[PDB]
């Protein structure tokens, strides 16, 4: 059903995986998925905006600036191996509403 635990992913692209990066130490924030392309690799890997990159190419993206993480990404040409961070449950359900009728 629903679950949320660490896990790595793999992308296939010379660089333009379709996803971007935003934040960093220089930014004063964690590395998150800036944007993504229509049904892009990242998307194909079920990557939503806000996903935090725990690692980049097996490297720790803890003490790495935006440029850094970007540098690594640039390093990767074949595939991109990075880890994401889970956050609570990733599923929402909208309840249906209805009203009675007058006689």
Image (tube, rainbow, N blue to C red):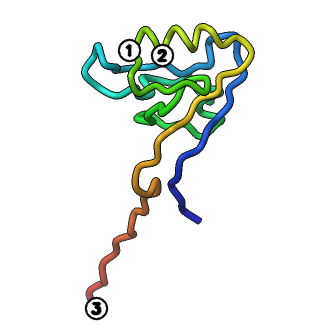
Residues packed near mark 3 inside 10 Å, few (<14), some (14 to 19) or many (20 plus): few
Q: Residue at x 59, y 33 (%)?
A: 43
Q: Which residue is mark 2?
A: 69
Residue 38, given in percent of the width and then of the height, sits at 58, 26
Residues packed near mark 2 inside 10 Å, few (<14), some (14 to 19) or many (20 plus): many
Whichever of labels 3 and 1 marks the residue nearer the N terminus, that label is 1
- The alpha-carbon separation of the residues under discs 1 and 2 comes to 6 Å
* Label disc, if present, on residue 17 of the rendered structure: none
4 lies above or below 63: below
Q: Secondary structure at mark 1?
A: loop
Residue 45, given in percent of the width and then of the height, sits at 64, 37
Residues packed near mark 1 inside 10 Å, few (<14), some (14 to 19) or many (20 plus): some
Q: Which residue is mark 3?
A: 103
> Mark 2 and mark 1 in contact (Cβ < 8 Å)?
yes
* Label disc, if present, on residue 65 of the rendered structure: 1
Give the quadrant of residue 95: bottom left
2 lies above or below 63: below
Mark in the foreground, 2 or 3: 2
Q: Residue at x 46, y 57 (%)?
A: 91
Give the quadrant of residue 27: top left
Q: Residue at x 41, y 27 (%)?
A: 62
- The alpha-carbon separation of the residues under discs 3 and 1 comes to 67 Å
Q: Secondary structure at mark 3?
A: loop
Whichever of labels 2 and 3 marks the residue nearer the N terminus, that label is 2
Mark in the foreground, 3 or 1: 1
2 vs 26, left or right, is right
């Amino acid at each position: 059903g629903s679950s949320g635990s660490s896990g790595s992913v793999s992308l296939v692209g010379p660089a333009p995986w379709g996803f971007r990066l935003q934040g960093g130490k220089d930014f004063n924030m964690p590395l998150t998925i800036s944007s993504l392309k229509d049904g892009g690799k990242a998307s194909q890997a079920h990557v939503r905006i806000g996903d935090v990159v725990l690692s980049i190419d097996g490297i720790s993206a803890q003490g790495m600036t935006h440029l850094e993480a970007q540098n690594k990404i640039k390093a990767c040409t074949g595939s991109l191996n990075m880890t994401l961070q889970r956050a609570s449950a990733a599923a929402k359900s909208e309840p249906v509403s209805s009203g009675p009728s007058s006689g």
